[PDB]
Image: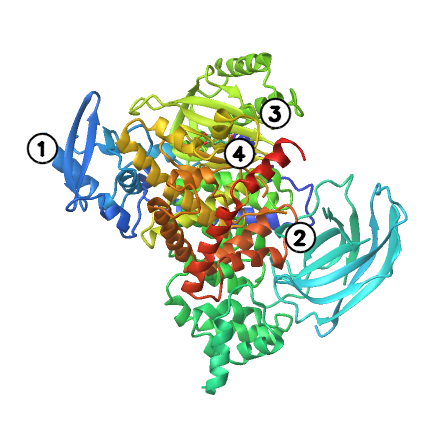
Amino acid sequence: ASEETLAFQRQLNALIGYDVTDVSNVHDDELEFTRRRLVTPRMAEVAGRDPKLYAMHPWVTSKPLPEYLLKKITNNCVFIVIHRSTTSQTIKVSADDTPGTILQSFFTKMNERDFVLRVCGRDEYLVGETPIKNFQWVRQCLKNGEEIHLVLDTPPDPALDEVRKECDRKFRVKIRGIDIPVLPRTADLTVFVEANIQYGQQVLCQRRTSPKPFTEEVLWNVWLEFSIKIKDLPKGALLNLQIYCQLLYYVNLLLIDHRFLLRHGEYVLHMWQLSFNADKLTSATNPDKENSMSISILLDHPIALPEMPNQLRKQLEAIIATDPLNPLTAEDKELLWHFRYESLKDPKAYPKLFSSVKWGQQEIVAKTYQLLAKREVWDQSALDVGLTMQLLDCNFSDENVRAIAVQKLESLEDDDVLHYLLQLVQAVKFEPYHDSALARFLLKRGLRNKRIGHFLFWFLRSEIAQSRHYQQRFAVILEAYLRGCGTAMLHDFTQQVQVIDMLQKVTIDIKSLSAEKYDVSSQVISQLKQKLENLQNLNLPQSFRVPYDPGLKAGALVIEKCKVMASKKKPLWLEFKCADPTALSNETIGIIFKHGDDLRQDMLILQILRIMESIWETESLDLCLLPYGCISTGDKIGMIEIVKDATTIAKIQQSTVGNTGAFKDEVLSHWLKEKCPIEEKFQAAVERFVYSCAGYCVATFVLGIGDRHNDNIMISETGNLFHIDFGHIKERVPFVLTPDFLFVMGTSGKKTSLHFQKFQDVCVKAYLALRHHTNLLIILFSMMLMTGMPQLTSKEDIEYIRDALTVGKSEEDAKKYFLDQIEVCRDKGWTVQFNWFLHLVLGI
Ligand SMILES: O=c1c(O)c(-c2cc(O)c(O)c(O)c2)oc2cc(O)cc(O)c12
């Protein structure tokens, strides 16, 4: 262990945000065991990735050009502007030419082929054997009807990515006692210990102890013998110890360790306090010992060795045809299991079929593995993310069952992996062991692609920072990725963390000045610009990669424009210059650092929104949403992308009117027209509004976050509406379709209109579009509530989304159901908003 070896670890831990070597909080060696087992897969991806292609991380898609983009193109032709210093030429190529057939054709028109096409002002290269039309930037430019400016520069040297040198007896447990240093005020409490043998979130068995008075020390020394036999215990089963006073304390212990051994010996586990969700499933113990409740137990080297009639048929398919949230009956399960090989021929049955398994029985499980052995039908089925996601949630704990889900994920191309990365990263919380297929799949895909890796870094880091329940597991996975991404990325991450940390302190040190009375003092803005000065001196990184948009390189601070927002939680409105000189503009980079809101929620919501945009893509729809970047940098803090030329709808009302609820109906249209002097840009901004508005209307409704204050919705000087603050979230409305909105669509009273009719038809089209992916949205929504909501979610919560999508209904009934929702908004006018103004603004 040279000084060099130690040094490396130190910085790694620094980047990680946690010390992955720490052992102060572990009752075994699973963590260390995983750090070692990931070394092979890590290296196995590193050496197998093309140095060049991994250096320029091309971003492409093998999906067909949507219909709304087909139009943007005229006769299989595209024009690209190539620049060389102040010399730039425009060329017209075929939408099927490769970036090489472009450079070659560029040397013809105007050592030798030692150059490459990069996007002006961005680290995004158009390279590889792929049609130019299959590059995201290209398709992005088309949609925005913008020009494609590329710069001819030198290809990065792959050397910069260099990687450093490398029993029939019934099971029984003994509860000795619980110890807690201090206790609650209401002190005439009573408590007992509930021991459960869980698996897949369902209890196979349960035992309890005699209730006793709640004291700083409670002994029992009672033997608890369950009914299930030691031989029946399935690998992945959990011994969930809980304390009731109402549940208050809980801790879990894997009965079968990572080595297939039966857990034994004396244990003193430090439990978690309850304030259902992902956290109640963790194997991790509470690190804080001096304050947490502790359970002392005892355990008894046993090793776990590695046709049908028409109405019956028609009743089987009826169950299989059921949605995800519909439970199963005793008969339901018995029917699914009896006909395993028949329910096996249909992939959409797997979830249902594998929950009908009696895992608490060695025999049944063994048969299951046999059943699974023959997976031709599955292996050859078409990838279905929604179906695959269902096998990765809290309902399954069998290593083999989950493994086949991951198996199908292997088919996803980088572009799609990017859409579901966040969700899949959260799914790790559902794994019973630190080392898993899903865990290795992510590690692998991160080392195989810089964009996937960049986000995998922050995604994991957000959880490492504010989740003591899973920071140990994630930290091991992050390290594994940091030990194989390269020295270049290892450097960017450093610059980014540095910039972040420094700005974090400031953001918080500024908020400390007035937290109950909005009033951005003149002196505060004076001190703010001062603290940044001290940093920009030479201590702050000259530049850094923007965490939510890695293709962008931020430079120096434009202290002049920086300020503290006139917001309650007083966030920071920072602006940077683009560190890239080849950029074709002078616009700054607006970044918002905020403390107070749980950005993990926004981050998750924003992601579903991106999932909905692509979903509409499959149907050739463009709702003009604006899922601005947002990354939870750490505990209660993170950044927010600033959308240029945009304001709050409320602000729009306040200017005309003021700090009153006497909302007008033309103010908005008067604000947009004023902004769009160029006529051709009004009707354009108007159609935009109709779509963006409709877009958010549909999406927001389905997610059950439509009733919202006028201050959390924004509009751009280009007519783009987009909801913002997704923080936590009598009269009520399905979504926001206020009079000022319907007005811009040329509709004063309850009278229809051309644009309003356009609006409606779009809403329906988008609404029906999502319904085709009901199952996908149902599972994502559920995982989100389980891993993204501080409180404990329930079935009721999940089922909402189901109703919103009107599952079971026909397209017609559906189409209508949404048109009625649109009506409520018309019959509610400014009612709701006025209430929000009265509630939020007045405190009533
Ligand atoms: O407090 C917030 C805020 O002010 C803005 C904002 C975004 C823009 O794009 C602007 O142009 C602007 O003026 C403000 O976004 C947010 C987005 C969130 O997810 C959460 C937030 O709390 C805010």
Q: Callout 3: helix, strand or loop?
A: helix
Proximity of marks 1 and 4: CB atoms separated by less than 8 Å: no
Q: Earlier in the sequence, mark 1 or mark 2?
A: 1
Mark 1: which amino acid? Lys
Q: Earlier in the sequence, mark 3 or mark 1?
A: 1
Residue where numbered disc 4 is placed: 711
Residue 280 numbered tag: 2
Amino acid type assigned to the residue bearing label 4 in the image: Asp
Kindly indicate whether the residue at mark 1 contacts the one at mark 3 (C-beta within 8 angstroms).
Answer: no
Q: Position of residue 98 (x, y in %)?
A: 20, 43
Q: Position of residue 713 (x, y in %)?
A: 49, 36
Q: Earlier in the sequence, mark 3 or mark 2?
A: 2
Would residue 144 be found to the left or right of residue 490 on screen?
A: left
Q: Mark 3, mark 1: which one is toward the viewer?
A: 3
Q: Nearer the viewer, mark 3 or mark 4?
A: 4
Which residue in the rendered view is the most extreme toward the bottom? 309
The residue to which callout 1 is attached is 109
Q: Is residue 415 among the parts visible in the rendering?
A: no
C-beta proximity under 8 Å, tags 4 and 2: no
User: Mark 3 belongs to which amino acid?
Assistant: Ile
Marks 3 and 4, how far apart at CA: 24 Å
Mark 3 residue crowding within 10 angstroms, few (<14) / some (14–19) / many (20+): some
Q: Residue placed at 40% from the left, 29% from the top?
A: 671
Q: Report whether 489 appears left or right of 621.
A: right
At label 2, counting other C-alpha atoms closer than 10 Å, the crowd grade (few under 14, some 14-19, many 20 or more) is some
Query: Disc 1 and disc 2: Cα gap in Å?
Result: 65 Å
> Which element is circle 4 on?
helix
- Total number of numbered labels? 4
Q: Which residue is mark 3?
A: 508
Residue at 50% x, 54% y is 780
